[PDB]
Image (tube, coloured by chain):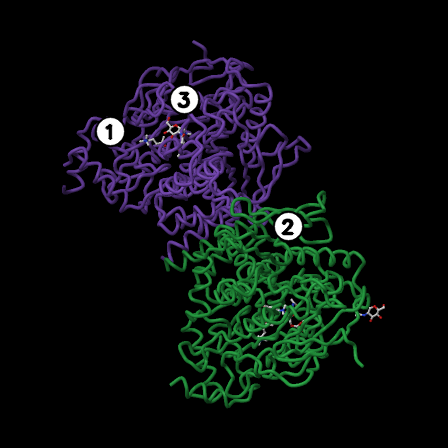
Chain colours: A purple, B green
Amino acid sequence: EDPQLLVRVRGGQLRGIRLKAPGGPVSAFLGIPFAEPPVGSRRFMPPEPKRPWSGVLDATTFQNVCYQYVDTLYPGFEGTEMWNPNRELSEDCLYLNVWTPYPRPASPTPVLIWIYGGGFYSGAASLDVYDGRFLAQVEGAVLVSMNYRVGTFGFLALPGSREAPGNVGLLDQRLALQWVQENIAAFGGDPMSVTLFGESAGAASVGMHILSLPSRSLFHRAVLQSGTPNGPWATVSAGEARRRATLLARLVGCPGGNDTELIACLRTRPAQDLVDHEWHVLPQESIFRFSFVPVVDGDFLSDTPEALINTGDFQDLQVLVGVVKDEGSYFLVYGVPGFSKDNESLISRAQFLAGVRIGVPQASDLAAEAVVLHYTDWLHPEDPTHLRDAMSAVVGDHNVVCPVAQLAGRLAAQGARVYAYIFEHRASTLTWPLWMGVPHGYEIEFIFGLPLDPSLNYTTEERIFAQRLMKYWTNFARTGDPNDPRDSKSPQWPPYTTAAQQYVSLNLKPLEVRRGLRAQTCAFWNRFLPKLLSAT
Amino acid sequence: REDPQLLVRVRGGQLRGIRLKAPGGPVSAFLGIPFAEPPVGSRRFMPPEPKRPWSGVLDATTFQNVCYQYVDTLYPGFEGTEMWNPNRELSEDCLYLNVWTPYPRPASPTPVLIWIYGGGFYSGAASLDVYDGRFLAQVEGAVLVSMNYRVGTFGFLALPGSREAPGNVGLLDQRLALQWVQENIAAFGGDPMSVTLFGESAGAASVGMHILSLPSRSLFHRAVLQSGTPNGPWATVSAGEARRRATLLARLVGCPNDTELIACLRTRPAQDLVDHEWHVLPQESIFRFSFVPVVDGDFLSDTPEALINTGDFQDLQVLVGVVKDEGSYFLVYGVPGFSKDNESLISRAQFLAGVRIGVPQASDLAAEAVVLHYTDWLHPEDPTHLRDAMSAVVGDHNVVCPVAQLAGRLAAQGARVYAYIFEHRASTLTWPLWMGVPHGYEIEFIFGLPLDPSLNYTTEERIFAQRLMKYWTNFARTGDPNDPRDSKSPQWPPYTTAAQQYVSLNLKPLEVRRGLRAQTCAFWNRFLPKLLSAT
Ligand SMILES: *[C@@H]1O[C@H](COC2O[C@@H](C)[C@@H](O)[C@@H](O)[C@@H]2O)[C@@H](O)[C@H](O)[C@H]1NC(C)=O
Ligand SMILES: *[C@@H]1O[C@H](CO)[C@@H](O)[C@H](O)[C@H]1NC(C)=O
Ligand SMILES: *[C@@H]1O[C@H](CO)[C@@H](O)[C@H](O)[C@H]1NC(C)=O
Ligand SMILES: *[C@](C)(O)CCC[N+](C)(C)C
Ligand SMILES: *[C@](C)(O)CCC[N+](C)(C)C
Ligand SMILES: CC(=O)CCC[N+](C)(C)C
Ligand SMILES: CC(=O)CCC[N+](C)(C)C
């Protein structure tokens, strides 16, 4: 019994496991329950705190993955499969993971809390890319990740109901945050220095915690990678949530009438029956749209993210935000005709016009015409390479890049300290084809430091790069500034402001400072298209 | 007892011209030749009638009267405005044309260039110094013809469907001059089977309307449109709008049945009409003119738009182009914040106000779309970017994108098209630097004025002028601006829908570029119409 691996938390004793990191050992405590299993009658309900336990709880292995859709687009393909559940599916899934330096840090260390993505319909903290051992060992950080309910189980809502009030998966996250405040000092973490970071729907989640007051006493800084609370996919109105939940119920045979009766019938259904019809409730043929997501309930979210970002005070907050070079490519293969991992995806103009209706599903005929006309290269209007890359750009700008620029600008104007980046390095080991470039999600492995494990076959320069990023992120966690406090120069990473709009490129070369994140194009999405809606 | 080489007979009778000095030698000039009956009195607003023959020898040694017009008062005494003002007496008796030819006249039939002046269809004269045909005549051996045509109410006031004021009579004045060339230009040594029209601004729009009107098409073979087009927001009005403007003008001068209204307008002093002419525009605007060509179903059988889209132009060669800063000239005539006497650094508020004045038909949404497209979102309040964006707005809307549209529709419908952008700022320009290369400041170079040493242009500008004169006359002669002998010099390739090629005209050798403001002209020519159409 290694005494470094025995910790007492409020709920009882835990036994961790010592893991090998390239530089030395780390202590891992995996599968720690932070909530009562949200099963049976607790389905769709807010999480309750985990009852204390007797003896020593085994925290040496990852717990079950929250019940979710499993991808079938390309069976056997690592590029999709690496995001799929790597443990058994269960509704009994509310557990978290802590990595710490071995031996336990002598003085309180900054804590980084990872929140995974997956369109609020998928994901798990147990995926290999979210492995906290490298950050813990090399940077001396305490790293935490939690499972939170996804799909219908996390986000099905009949707004105003006691039984399915909405946003319970975000309440799962918050409960893990409260757990860290209460318990993390036992692992050597500093609860007065907590930094949330996440990607895609995880980044959106981090932004939802910034915009919800009860969460604000639970962290000090935030990192939003390729995702935002504002924007077209991350939230729904109460009316639309109700409509989707009612349709799903009808599809599985429930009950209509009374919320209580409808929700009671939904609780009788096998979990896979709910997942089988999850996708059939979206109003349009679309991509980058997800059926069950956070809802503007007037509680967790007191108003729309738009309203809350525009009128908030963010003076004692520091934020790091950014995007990858090709945010849209990933999603095109899941719905737009002409696109595939298995060919160069050179498309016709006709296929481009069609793809825009699917990639921008809420667009009117006139707004879709505006998008086609703005993204067409009028010197090469029917060139398939341009049309393919423009399709990627539309989806990426609409859903990620322009939402990020919006948020960055409002936070900075409202008093926040903001740093921005674009991530431009494509992994040498990527299994997706070249045309997809640097796809959504493929920065994470670098930030978590996987290239430091030589068994994985990254290059030497990829390892040096990973180490740079791990430092930016942990420096930001420590101080709210990603710049190294004693290293003279590297050119410095400047704060993003509304006047100068400075951001940096993260690639194999030294930091380069640029001005304006797609400034002209994001004026189209963020300023003009809204007026085109209001006017007509 | 007088110079035998200056005496010539035309259909109407005998003429006596004058021997003028050009720097490389003498030229012959026949100035003030009448081609129509004076459009005065009961003939006001009526189509032109051919000139009745005269007895004896008509003196054609001086320019005739300028067609009655508004005289610019913006900057009194200032050469930049005054050079475009009338330089002879204003009269409604103004339908005269001018011919320049080599001295002695050519022995073999020579290609003819016909100049049609601009000035918004409200102004201009063939007698202005910048339209001096002596250098083209002397240096290129050209026969150059320029006519006066009626402008303003006199040329373009229309009550459509009426007999007495049918509209477009200023265009008919031009047409009659073209008919005169066909009948008479051989007497001067010109080739009536090789006639090239060229003109600038409204003059260019006019050339385009001759292309689109069948009776004119038998009267020339090739065309050059400089900074203007028949299509676009300013060159034509609908029948209904012409009538509305005609009728309001009538009211403002005390003329409340078409025959009666028109009979009453014919009794009014010409100056009374000019004095109220600007009051009939529907909006506070720039680059808009009260009395212009009307879509009458006759001269123009349909809208220039419909005619460029459905025409067969297989037998047409055209040279078209623009200057670097089409919009700047117009800003000082009505956008608050702009002046010749300072740098015109404007605020964002002044930019938004200026967009409404420069795009006066735009709804609020279209105007917002224009502002967002032309804003630099990195420096959205920078007064220098805002000034220059105001300029680009007015220029792209009124000139550059209409020209792009015309060039593409002509090329797709079978025409051979050549396109340019003119980028040299005359060293002698009196407008301030911020105005760049303004609308109209290519003309002096094409006409070869730098060749006159009294004008103080640079040596490099003389050589540039000579190059331009060659492109224009080569095109006139062969329908190709390139010299067939000169191989290694860069070539000017035709404009096509696929490649969109065009050349820069400056002190450097020809540089081929691709796409004439392709992205921005997509906004003006493809999107804004759909925004209108949907709303
Ligand atoms: C630029 O001039 C505009 C036109 O009015 C004037 O011209 C200038 C040169 C001054 O002499 C003024 O006193 C004249 O009235 C002004 O409207 C504009 O505000 C001027 N620009 C600035 C910011 O000074
Ligand atoms: C690429 O692959 C998919 C399926 O194999 C196919 O549907 C698509 O048409 C292909 N691309 C083209 C347009 O050749
Ligand atoms: C041209 O230059 C001369 C000599 O310096 C000067 O006196 C004359 O006024 C100038 N003329 C013009 C046309 O500006
Ligand atoms: C985002 C909307 O959550 C999508 C993220 C998808 N993976 C594959 C990166 C997890
Ligand atoms: C055009 C609309 O006719 C304007 C031409 C103006 N000048 C000053 C160049 C003649
Ligand atoms: C991977 C996605 O973004 C969506 C997958 C869901 N469908 C396969 C039903 C589109
Ligand atoms: C120079 C022009 O474009 C027209 C000016 C006419 N007003 C001075 C009456 C506005």
In percent of width and height, residue B339 lies at 65, 69
Image position, residue A256 (x, y; %): 14, 41
Say which quadrant the N terminus of chain A sits in.
top left
Measure the C-alpha gap from mark 1 to mark 2.
62 Å
Q: Considering depth in this image, is A122 or B107 the residue closer to the camera?
A: B107
Task: State whether discs 3 and 1 lie on one chain.
Answer: yes
Q: Nearer the viewer, mark 3 or mark 2?
A: 2
Looking at the picture, how far across and down is residue A210, in whole percent? 43, 41
Ligand 3 falls in quadrant = bottom right
Q: Is mark 2 within 8 Å of ligand 5?
A: no
- Residue to which mark 1 is pinned: A276
- How many neighbours does mark 1 have within 10 angstroms: few (below 14), some (14-19), or many (20 or more)? some
What crowding class fits label 2: few (fewer than 14 Cα within 10 Å), some (14-19), or many (20 or more)? many
Q: Are marks 1 and 2 on the same chain?
A: no
Which residue shows up at 36% across the image and 27% down it? Answer: A147
Under mark 1, the amino acid is Asp
Q: Is residue A41 above or below residue B10?
A: above
Quote the CA–CA distance across marks 3 and 1.
Answer: 22 Å
Which residue is identified by label 2? Answer: B503
Q: Is residue A469 visible?
A: yes
**In terms of depth relative to the viewer, which is nearer, A331 or B510?**
B510
**Which one is in front, B384 or B27?**
B27
User: Residue pushed farthest top?
Assistant: A1
In the drawing, what numbered circle is on residue A82? 3
Determine which quarter of the picture holds residue B499.
top right
Residue A320 % position (x, y): 52, 37
Q: Chain of mark 3?
A: A
Q: Is residue B370 above or below residue B149?
A: above
- Residue kind at label 3, given as amino acid type: Met
Label 1: chain letter: A
- The answer to whether marks 3 and 2 sit on the same chain is no
